[PDB]
Every structure is written in structure tokens, then in C-alpha cells.
Image (cartoon, rainbow over all chains, first blue to last red; front, side):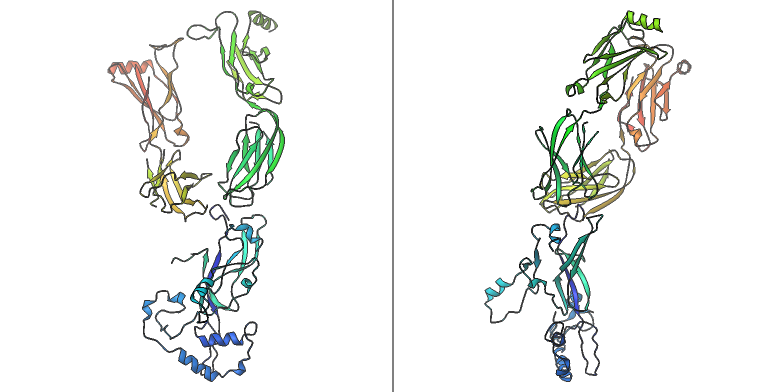
Length: 106
Length: 106
Length: 191
Length: 191
């Protein structure tokens, strides 16, 4: 604190969110990063027990859910990535690798 | 918080920014009542819901919940503050805004 | 914080800054003055004293009230101090100490047998009473010829009688304003 | 906007006003000074330069930081400037240039065969080194009698030898303070 900053400002931040257990049809569980996919978002929120619904994972059919994600990650072509400069803040980790899917959620 | 107020202009001394400003609209709402209930700010005085931790997936901007404030004994100009932000292991912080001013140039 | 008068110019007030960082200036009200002092907070440091000088007051009872002003214009509660002020110790040097029995052109030896001296009244007699002038007269040996106290008067006459007596018991002159309480001219005037 | 130092007194800072109309004053921090300059915005015009003078600094590296203050007390980002300051070119005129070999009353012709001169040191020697005094001596014909440089010294002696030699190769006097960098008294003093 000094004559040029006579008070503390408000503080808010931009962050990249919780890591989620994305599955793969081969039986891996990458669990490494955020995912923009709404299914894996829902699954984490439901199976969390510290918060959320406290549902045990054994009640879900993984071989079904992975097909649903394979639907929801279909590529769109109504636009092209170069029209989106923000992309890093939009959530894409690389502007060149396809970042386009029917649905992306933040 | 009652300590932190002694370092803020009367504009702010107990105010806080809201979270998830645009909750989902549906035909259940009147257009007016929706946009009139969309609200930017809250007062923590007489409000407890503000202090619930949010969960984030993808990229978002969120306000910090203060949980500790103090000054170095010899030099009251030096102020430490702790802001809690988000549940779980996040992929990480990207940026900070002090007031609305971001560190990185727009 | 820690508002404190301090004697030596009559003295200084001093204080440590308010911890409310939006403070822009301090105001001081002094008993019997028409208007407050105003003291800017151009730098902020919580351990560094600010100061105001008090100058030209007579010795006497006074009270001081000091208030911080916030940028929104409201003020702290006052702090009060009540004290006796005292005379400025370091008086002016006497001015125009001069010899009146002096020739056309200018003197080395003066005119006539015995000198006649004048000087001009100091400012401080306007405020502090019982000031006097102290005068000392010396030969080239710098022995005492004569030493004199002059009470609120600005002229003195040396005499051929005085020269004779001082010689018989056996020029340069120095004079200063003086008082009690250590009140003195900071230096001698001299001829 | 367009914060700019400008040389000639060491020089002037200048800038164009901030476009944020609630600006009340600018503050300037100068390297090594105890306190900022403060400059009011008593009139608003977006194309009119504001100015601050820089006076009495020695030549040397300095930095300046300038900030606008909004009526709410917050400040802009700073603008910074770093530059070498340089000597004030226009020095004081020499004072009390006077002849010491002078009679009771006052002289026309001086006393004795050859003049003895004194003058009083200028202020600028307190700041800028390698100042000197330049002295020139002339007859009623205003021919050169003699020209002299005096190094940080405040007296000089003319001589009957000098008068004789200057006559044989063949009064009025003028003197000025001077230096490098165009440092000069704005005018001659003279007798």
C-alpha cells in the first residue's frame, strides 16, 4: 500500500477448471485434464461424494457412455478455427489442431 | 472480512460480485423477470450463500472468497490476504483481474 | 498517533501518520489564531513523523487540536494537547550598530573625544518583555574596557571620563540582544 | 501525453493533458528530490501543453516520473523519462565589484599608483565547477589595456608595472562570471 494505491482493489481471476476422468473405449482412464464434454462433466459431478450426488460408478455402463461421447464430439464444419482469436481463453489448447465439436461447455 | 473492510472504499466495504450470472433461461420464466433477476452483485452481510465454493469445468472467470487478512507487524503497509477460489484440483490459474483491470493486455 | 509538542521559534508539533491510508492532509487549530495550519500527506510511511513548526508566539498557555481529513471530507475524532509555550531562545542579531559622532566621509578615529553609539531595535521586543542589550568595549589588547547593560534603549554614550578611568586602571565594541530563559542574539554585532 | 524534457535554469518538462477530464493535478517525482512537484489543471484544453520548470540542478543523470491524479485519488500508470540535465547557461551578474585602494569619502582617481579589486562570489559556483571570472580593463579610448582570467578567486591586483607596460605599448573595468558550455553572466558588471 502506497500513495499510488490507496486501497486494495477487488480481486477476481480466470482459471482452467477441475480435472475429470475421461474414459476411453480401450479401457484407459486418462483422468489428466479438464474436458469440455458434457458427459464427462456430468459423470464427475454425479460420482463426486464430497459434493454432488454421491453415486457409485459401478451403476454406470461405460461402454454406453463412451458411445455417447463419440456422438457429442462429432466435428462441425460450419466455421473454421481461424475466425476465433480468443481460442486459448475459449478453452482450446491449440488453435491449429481441430478444436471444433458440436458442443463445447465452460 | 470485518478486518478487510478497513482497507476499502465505502463503495465496496462488504460487497461481492455474484457467481453464475446467467442461469439457464426456460419457458418457465418471463423474459422480463429473468433479465431483472440476473444480478451482478451481492452483499455478504446477511448473505451466507455467497460463501459456498463453486465448481468449474472448462474456462471461467470467478471472484475470490477472502478467508484471511492481516498486516506485517512492523510495516502496516504490507498486507497479506488469502482468497479461496475453486473446488478440487484445477488445471490452473490463467490470469488475475484487479478491479476490472487484467494484468495481460487485451 | 502520538501527537507531541516539543520545545526548541517556539517549538515543533510532531505526530505519526494516521493508519487510514486515504488521509490527504492534517489540520491543526491553535488557540487564538484565526485559521488552522494545513499539512499535506505527500508521502505515506507508517513509522515516519510529520512535523509542524510553531514560531513567533509569546510564552503562554495554548491548546492545539489536530484532525485528519479523509478524501471524502469527513474527519477523525480530534486529538487535543494543552501546554505552556516558551520564548524563542535564538534571537536576532542587532542591526545598524553605528557611531553617530562621525566625520564627513568616514571615520577611523572617531570625531571628538568620546563615542556616541546607536543601534536599531530587534523584532523580538514586540513579543517578549524584559529584553535588554548587552554591550562590551575592548582595547586592541582585547582587555575589558567596559561592560554595560542597556534596558530597552537603543543608544549609549562613551565618555572621556570613562576612557580616562579605564586607561588609568589599565577601540572595539560588540553588542547583543539578551534576556532571561537563555534568550540571546545568535551572535554578537560589533564595530 | 507526449511527456518531453527540453533544455534551456536547467530546462522545462512539458506534456499534453490527459484526456480523462476529471484530472485535477499532475504530480512529478524527480530522482533524488525529497518531494514531488504538483501542477494544477486550472484550465482544460486537449491541445495545449502544460509545463514545469527545472532550475538549479547540476548537470547529471536524472529520471522523472509523472502521474495524473483523478478527483477520486487514484492515478494513471506512470510515464517515465531518463535524461542528462545540463548547466544553466545564463549565470548571475557579478556583484559588489569594488576597488579597495579607495580614499575617505569616495574616489574619482583612486588612491595610490595601482588599483586593487574585489568582487563577491556568485551563487552558481555552489553547483557548477570550473567557473571562472573574466576581467577586462580599458582606457578612455576603450582600447585594450589588459584582459585576465581569475580561477575561483575574488580579488585581483593591478600594478604600476602593468600600467607602465600597457601605456608603453599604447580607467574602466568590466568583469563577468563565465564557464564552458556557454556558461556566462547575462551581463558584464563594470566600474
